[PDB]
Image (cartoon, rainbow over all chains, first blue to last red; front, side):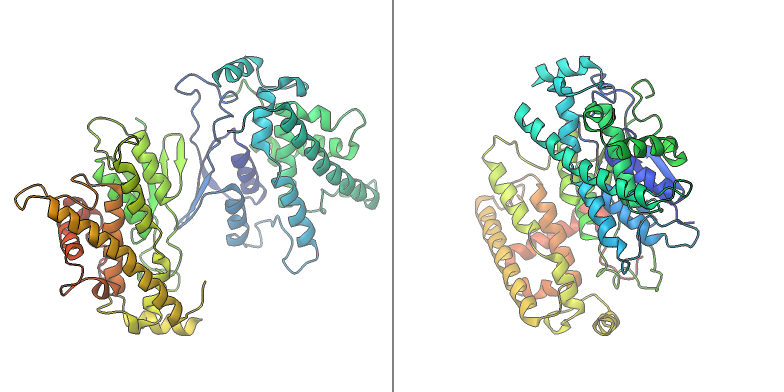
Amino acid sequence: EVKLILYHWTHSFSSQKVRLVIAEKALKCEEHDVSLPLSEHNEPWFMRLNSTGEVPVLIHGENIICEATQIIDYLEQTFLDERTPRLMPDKESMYYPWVQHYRELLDSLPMDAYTHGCILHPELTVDSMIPAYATTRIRSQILDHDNVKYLKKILDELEKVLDQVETELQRRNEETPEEGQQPWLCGESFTLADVSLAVTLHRLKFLGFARRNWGNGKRPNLETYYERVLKRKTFNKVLGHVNNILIS
Amino acid sequence: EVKLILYHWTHSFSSQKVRLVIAEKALKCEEHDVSLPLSEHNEPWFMRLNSTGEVPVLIHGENIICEATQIIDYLEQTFLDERTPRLMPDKESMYYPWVQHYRELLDSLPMDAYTHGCILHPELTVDSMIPAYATTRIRSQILDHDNVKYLKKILDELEKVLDQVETELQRRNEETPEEGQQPWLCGESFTLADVSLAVTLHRLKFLGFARRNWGNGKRPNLETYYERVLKRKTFNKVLGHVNNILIS
């Protein structure tokens, strides 16, 4: 039969979203982790995050797509079996603009900039999971140069995106009955915007910028969202150990 | 050992150049032809040329590149063994500007536009190898719309690129002794610009625009170049039967 194939770096933002979509849609893929346990210079996966995560690539028989966003879209378009769950509304529906908006909003964030801003400029992190011995190595080894001003700017922009999200989630909470199917950001169905939000929050925690953005009575609906998605079966299967620096 | 892998459409301009580079550099790859012998609608490979040729993808252990030009560059950069022949001059050399210039010159051509301009607007072709039954199917089935003016414009631009090439080849002929190692476009070494020129000319013949551009005393040095490269072992191994509509 025509088989799905994927070549990816397990510890990569792109691959994380793609694999989560493959699991949400119940699709069976032949995932191949191409990442090395240790680099030529014996850099673990966390010290290697600076290195490009290598955009993933899907091979569906004859078709070939190589980009997280594109591969995700292709999976949605090609697998239309009634059993396969859909992670997007119908184009005609009045949901699609909102869903796509928030997906883009969260996909526009410069995660690559953050990942380098915690290794560097580590004072802006809180409870970062990246070993500090990587900071010194990167700082001395020497992409955009290190400007605390720049890093502080994009993090203030991250606050804006997450503030919008927090508002929408609060609206969801007000609408839903206490005892009832709790909805996600856009609706009761797990959308593509939810896979972006979920992976974003998870990576942010690895960087330590999570505590600053939500917690201790800040963005409470966002805090609840994160604890909820951490328990989801799909999340713990794909992204479960992706933040553990020991497992690699 | 770290192995090379490639997923490609045998009858695709991109894959043709890449596979030719892999052969010129003597590298061993695990090429996988993903193209189908016949489509879902039973369209042979030539009637399927309209369909995107699917950019190829190289997987070198941990590294992943998915674009003809990029994959070619990567192969040049990563395989630096003395045995591996180099298809480019040294960056410092005064050759590199010229070589890269002609490579870009020939890579800028809109081959995708030509491939659709011969199926459509077939009067501009001469001895086209595409069965004419594909023309009628495409013309009625209905990317940029069909304007004879547009097609005639880009073909006049193709004449300019090939006229430059013809001039450079004439200079090569004047420099070289009759009895001596005949040089290619840029020098005695087979460059990346030569793989572009070679595959370009070969595809053009499949489209029928070859006769118009060279032949019968027109661009004689270019005609000689084409007959010469057709005999090259690397060419007949990779691109040998890529223009034969029977072999598929």
